[PDB]
Image (cartoon, coloured by chain):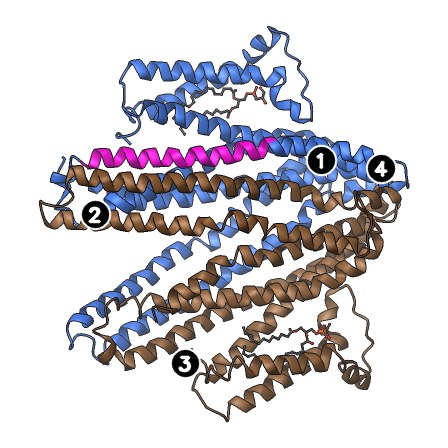
Chain colours: A brown, B blue
Amino acid sequence: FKSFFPKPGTFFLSAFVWALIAVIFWQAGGGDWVARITGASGQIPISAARFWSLDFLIFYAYYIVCVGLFALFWFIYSPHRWQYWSILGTALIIFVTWFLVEVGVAVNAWYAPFYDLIQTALSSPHKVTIEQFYREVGVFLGIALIAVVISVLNNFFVSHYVFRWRTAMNEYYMANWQQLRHIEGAAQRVQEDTMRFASTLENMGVSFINAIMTLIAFLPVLVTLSAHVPELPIIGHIPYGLVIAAIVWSLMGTGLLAVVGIKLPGLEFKNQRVEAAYRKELVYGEDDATRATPPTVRELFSAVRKNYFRLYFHYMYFNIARILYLQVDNVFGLFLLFPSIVAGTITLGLMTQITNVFGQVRGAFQYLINSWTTLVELMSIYKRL
Amino acid sequence: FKSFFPKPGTFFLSAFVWALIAVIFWQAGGGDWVARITGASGQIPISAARFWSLDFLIFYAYYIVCVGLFALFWFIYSPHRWQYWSILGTALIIFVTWFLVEVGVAVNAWYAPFYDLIQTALSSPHKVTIEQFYREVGVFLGIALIAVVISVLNNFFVSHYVFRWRTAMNEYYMANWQQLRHIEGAAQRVQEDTMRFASTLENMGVSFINAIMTLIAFLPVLVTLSAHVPELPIIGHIPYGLVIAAIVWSLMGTGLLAVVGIKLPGLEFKNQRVEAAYRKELVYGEDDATRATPPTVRELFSAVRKNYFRLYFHYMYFNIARILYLQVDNVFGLFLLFPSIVAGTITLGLMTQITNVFGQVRGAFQYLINSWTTLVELMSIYKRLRSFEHELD
């Protein structure tokens, strides 16, 4: 961190403070202030033309100015020679991660008009025309084309960004190679731990910040869709019944599913430990006739057998919870809507829009169980350095 | 292979010959001969009672007798230490892989009645009742409960199955360690390469055999569903137009997508080559103070940087093709059905059933590419094991 980041003690803190000041000036007052001055309409089209509308273009100017003010503060205070990749570089990655969420809510808002058109078509033959369907696909391809261009440039940029981190650290380590040479375990602390640190930290950083963004974007649309689901199957009418049930079910994908699988990383460590122990007796067996004695290697293999057999049995418990959850998840999204489907309040557009937002919110809490590898791996690497 | 399978030269081939004889006696007659006896039923329920209907469990008897006859031939001729795991163990994995395909077909056939009920409900309020919906989701949980209890026992068995392969190899390499001692890297090949061989070979073995089964199971239903889609969007009426368009689009995940990404495995190798060269230069500089120097390590790292940069640029081409395919695939399944949706010849149930078939068939061709990748990885591992026998022969 000391390399590739200007003073990480006050950086990552002045950034977080500045983010809250900018957000409070936008989402808790203000925001409409600049929008009213410029005369923004305040309406957002479902088409791909939303991304260059006046409402969105205001945010782009605000983001650049706020980052520009933040950059100019650090571009004079403590220059670091990696500013344009450390401060400006990560600002683009945060912004692009937010933009790729707005394309997600754009297609989600597109299912409501598209599938309401399918429902109209199936109810009566030739009530709609074929030319009406093509202009609905032609709108989705506008959003999809934007997502394709931004996503490929996002992965292209972030891959250099993590590589400029290795270039920065190796520049610092090599300049002190005369003292760091004698340290045991080198030539992988500088050759293998540099990438596995930068690559995994960025992966955790974007994934964690993507979870917050996709919850901020998709919880409000669940709330505004909860007006069309007044009642739930078994518990009857409950205020905000849809979002409360959506949150609780989504936690099951990272709660009970993670509780039963918390012992798996512990058992995995023991298996690789006994594998390394088997290696140690095997490597000494090559150089000498003694060691790797056939009575002895039988002991080490009987020790790796039992540790694998215990992992297989414990992973069976995790498989039952995970597989059953996925199978039920195919119909739980539709299960909640049964008292509303029968009542005629929900149309086909909302039924597939509500089903879609369930997956996106589920993919948010997925960034706890699925990212758990990165959270523990970051500390597994930062301790060596 | 010789340490686990009995005479892999013939058994691993005679099994394929025996399968064709058993299949020809089943799918080209004979199956009706044994179904005519005992009456059978002919029809198949959509419920979870599908898997013990008279149509199926006669096939279970046929499978057991055929593998039992095949195994009995190899248990009398050329006996082996790992007979039950190598022959009966492999046969169960093949059968369970087939069974989970029939579970996927069962839920796919369940979409037609369920979604035709949703379409009925949305067209007129209170034309359906809530209890009518609970019965439809009731029969799905019956199939899902069968799926989970067989899938977890499948992974439990196959994980033990690959370990009996590793146990088999070590029992053969040990007691020969006195001759294999002097080979370079013998320790890591007897520990790491003997596990990554069995672990990845089964991944290729089941994925390749899963792709064939899910194509054999889902192409006929796709052809049957093609009667409800007489016309295609642009090309007009085409015989079997749905399945022809489904296959061509599914090959796009193995054609254009694979062609642009063919250079990636080759380009990745050079990256790890230069990176291992960097490690090699560092280790020699760790022992000798004059080996690293401010030059050389600067120059050789510049070869690491200039080689990664060509991977990022080339992977950008693969991203455009892959991401665009996935984005379009969200609506291409519905694009073909547009002239049929407007014509009223299709319902909501068939629209979801046809769309679901596209995903399963697409995953079949996905399984073939992953099978090829696992096979080429296996060759990278099999060469080490093939060469390891230097001293034995």
What range is drawn magenta here?
B146-174
Tell me which label, 1 or 2, sits earlier in the chain.
1
Q: Tag 4: residue type?
A: Thr
Q: Relative to residue A226, is residue A333 depicted above or below?
A: above
Rendered-image quadrant of the N terminus of chain B: top left
> For the residue labelled by badge 1, is the local secondary structure a helix, a strand or a loop?
helix
Badge 2: how crowded within 10 Å, few (<14), some, or many (20+)?
Answer: many
Q: CA distance from mark 2 to mark 3?
A: 40 Å
Expressed as whole percent of the image width and height from the top left, the position of residue A289 reads: 8, 45
Of circles 1 and 2, which is in front? Answer: 2
Q: Which residue is mark 3?
A: A2
> For the residue labelled by badge 4, is the local secondary structure a helix, a strand or a loop?
helix
Badge 4: how crowded within 10 Å, few (<14), some, or many (20+)?
Answer: some
Residue A146 appears in the picture as rendered: no
Q: CA distance from mark 2 to mark 4?
A: 67 Å
Expressed as whole percent of the image width and height from the top left, the position of residue A205 reads: 52, 68
Q: In this rendered view, identify the residue nearer to me: B131 or B313.
A: B131
Task: Give the quarter of the image for residue B206.
Answer: top left
Q: Tag 2: residue type?
A: Ala
Q: Which residue is mark 1?
A: B111
Q: CA distance from mark 3 to mark 1?
A: 57 Å
The subunit carrying tag 4 is B
Badge 1: how crowded within 10 Å, few (<14), some, or many (20+)?
Answer: many
What residue do we see at 49% from left, 83% from top? A84
Q: Relative to residue B244, is residue B16 depicted above or below?
A: above
Pointer 1 with pointer 2, Cβ within 8 A:
no
Q: Is residue B221 left or right of residue A343?
A: left
